[PDB]
Image 1 (spheres, rainbow over the protein chains, first blue to last red):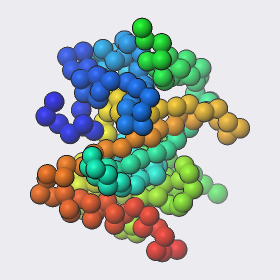
Image 2: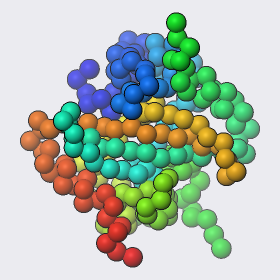
Image 3: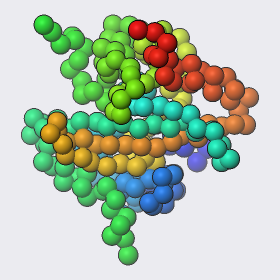
Image 4: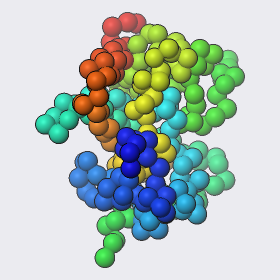
Length: 110
Length: 116
């Protein structure tokens, strides 16, 4: 689409591959999403349960380690971090199952 | 003796402001592996009330982009279960504002090294 990559929202009409590229093993590639989530984006039935872990803009810049890398491909704002699950949430076990369904799911794609 | 009165939201959903600053919401800036390193004294104190916040927030990802672009993992450790993330967001080097964006981001990256 015409938006900067980081502001795109994937849906059935403009899916994860279209917005964010194929899943893969490279540092530059995303690794998250089974075939259903890839094709459906935010239309995926359990999208809200995934999105609850995504950071607000304030938390993205507040929690992460932020860097800047200048490479031949361009200038990149790098980010890394970790978000703790609330194991006192009764939904904790469902959250673990859901994340396990999508993290590196492309390793099973035919 | 207390938790901050604005701390009810999960950490990743918090919004820092003058009333709930970056240190209060997200911890002291520092060098350690999962510790935040971003913000000068003005941004730390003001959070999203910082007058140039929109020019920083233009680089933050939507929830869909966060899960679509990043490398996501999960780790179970003695402290709990953690969703790990890494990624990179490309700046538009053809934007006339590009040089100013770089200056603004660099002003905040590791700024904590220069003050107590």
